[PDB]
Amino acid sequence: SATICRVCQKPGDLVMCNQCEFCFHLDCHLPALQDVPGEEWSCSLCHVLPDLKEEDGSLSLDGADSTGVVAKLSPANQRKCERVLLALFCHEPCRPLHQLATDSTFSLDQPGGTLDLTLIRARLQEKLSPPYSSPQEFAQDVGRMFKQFNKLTEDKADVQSIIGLQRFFETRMNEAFGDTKFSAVLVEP
Ligand SMILES: [Zn+2]
Ligand SMILES: [Zn+2]
Image (cartoon, rainbow, N blue to C red; front, side, top):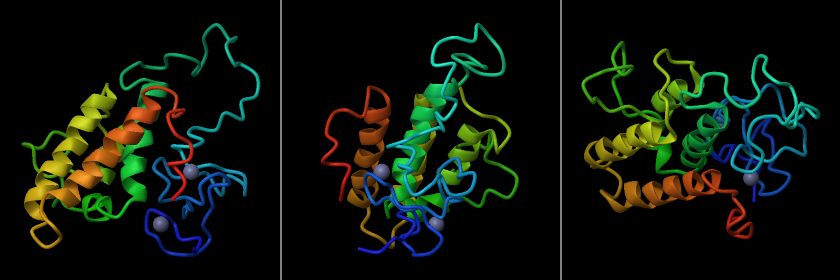
């Protein structure tokens, strides 16, 4: 198997999941890496936000971020949906998804247009503008993604391409929303 930014599935200056070969161009990394998270990284579904903070594991009282910087989508809850957009990101069905809309200047609150991983991701990321407040808000969108994903595709499978991704979606979304301790032998293709 090649490095390939699992997302893109293209080789390069990718970063292989020291745990599940999940390589990433970094930038394609859901929240986009910082610059190669070391050859010991582990996806975002496997590693998520850089915990390198070392300390402040539960002691900081309150500063820039510890347990609730906004609690919108919340640091970690945002991280979960990010465990998703990513989950999505990584697979193929999402590839179409990443880019479905005609965005231009309407997705932030567009009339339920088409969204896409990146759409949602930016939200999640705050890259966008209007960030959600729930990985279900998110999921709702990606779930939308999926909706129009399934209606726009028309070239791929139809549903089950969407769905298989829609399941994947909910899988990591399920992982993140628990402990991703379910099955570590299933995260390794
Ligand atoms: Zn890539
Ligand atoms: Zn991984």
